[PDB]
Amino acid sequence: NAKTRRHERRRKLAIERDT
RNA sequence: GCGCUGACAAAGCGC
């Protein structure tokens, strides 16, 4: 199951929204 | 395993 593969790219953006 | 929601979760739900 693709948890980490999706997460990696989504994470960068998710963080950068809050930032 | 790859998406897709979610906490950048776990879990779910497609392919």
Image (cartoon, coloured by chain):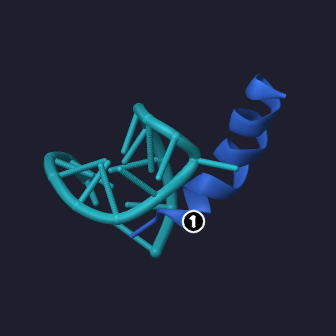
Chain colours: A blue, B cyan
Counting from the top left corner in percent of width and height, residue A3 is at: 48, 62
Q: Is residue B6 above or below residue B10?
A: above
Marked residue chain, label 1 = A
Q: Residue at x 75, y 35 (%)?
A: A13
Residue in view at x 75 percent, y 38 percent: A15
* Relative to B7, B12 lies left or right: left
Indicate the amino acid at tag 1: Thr
Residue on which disc 1 sits = A4
Horizontal relation, residue A10 to residue A15: left or right: left
Up-down relation of residue B9 to residue A11 (above or below): below
Observer-nearest of B4 and B15: B4
Residue A7 position in % (x across, y down): 60, 54
Vertical relation: B4 (above or below) A11? above
Image-quadrant location for residue A5: bottom right
- Residue B6 placed where, x, y %? 44, 35
User: In front here: B10 or A13?
Assistant: B10
Q: Residue at x 38, y 70 (%)?
A: A1
Q: Residue furthest front?
A: A19
Q: Secondary structure at mark 1?
A: helix
Name the residue: 69% across, 57% down: A8
